[PDB]
Image (spheres, rainbow over the protein chains, first blue to last red):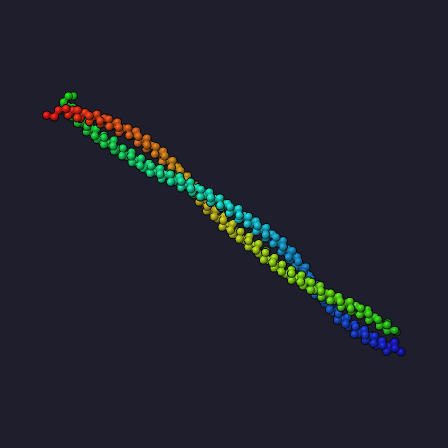
Length: 142
Length: 136
């Protein structure tokens, strides 16, 4: 009669196996839907890095430009400065000249005032000598 | 009516061995993605350090450029002050030349006008003693 005596053992065999499978798909469906989230986190983080690298790339340019800007205003301040230290030396020069020129004009003006008295002394001498010659000349000859 | 030779177990048993190794495959693809996720987390960090450095470096340069630019303004007005002083003094120097010459020309014509008096004076004297000719 067998065709039922062990159709019980068939359906029971299918029972045990089947819900082994059940369990396994439960793992399948889950593992791969969970992974799918972790794998979309990678696809977001790869683009995040992609921007951030065309960002860091701009920041480096922006900063190399800002350093060149600084190196140029600062070479420009080496030059104005050396040109100011020249102007300074040309004003000191030209003003240590004045200072010698004014000590020159000082001694010469002392000579001029001094020679101005001399004409005033002799003018006193002569007037007296012209008087006492008209005197000693009236007391006698003509 | 043969209990379809209960091999219909293989319909769900072959897909049991399959669905079982597949799963252990996703265990692998799980790990690989984990590692590539850590790696990636690190370079994103190194990218933040380098993005900031690039912002500092640039902020540094912008500050220094302003400090410099202000010093220019100052050395420059000071250069114009040094020039104007070099120029006023140059003109002073020049007035003094003219005046040292205007003074020397008078100091000479007046050196003569003194030797001239001294001749007048010389003869009046050589004559005061000349009219003294007579002492008792």
